Length: 107
Image 1 (cartoon, helix red, strand yellow):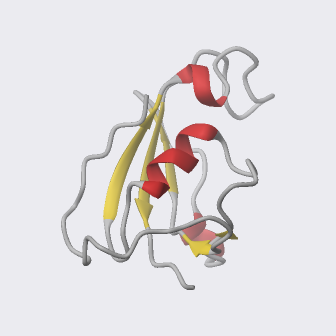
Image 2: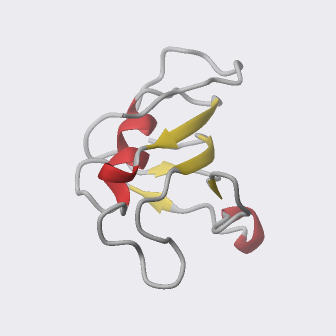
C-alpha cells in the first residue's frame, strides 16, 4: 500500500509518463527511527526513469500519483520493498518506510 499526504503546491496536471526521466529530492526515514538515506547531502538529485523497476515498488507507484512541484509523503509497506529479506546492514527485515519526496522533474 502506497498512501500520499500532499503538501499542496504545484500544478496538479503535469503527470509523469512511461520512459520519462524524473528528478526527485528524496529523503528516507525509518518509522520510529532515524534517517537512512538522503539526496540532500550529495546534491545529486537522482535522475531516474519510469517503467524499468530500477527503484522499489512503493517508491515507484507514489511517484506516478504526483505532479510537478508537489511534495508528497510516502508510506511503504514492508511487503513491497524489503520486509521479507531486509537490506543487509541498512534496512532490517519487516520494516515500514517513510519518504519525503519532492518531484521537480524534466521532460
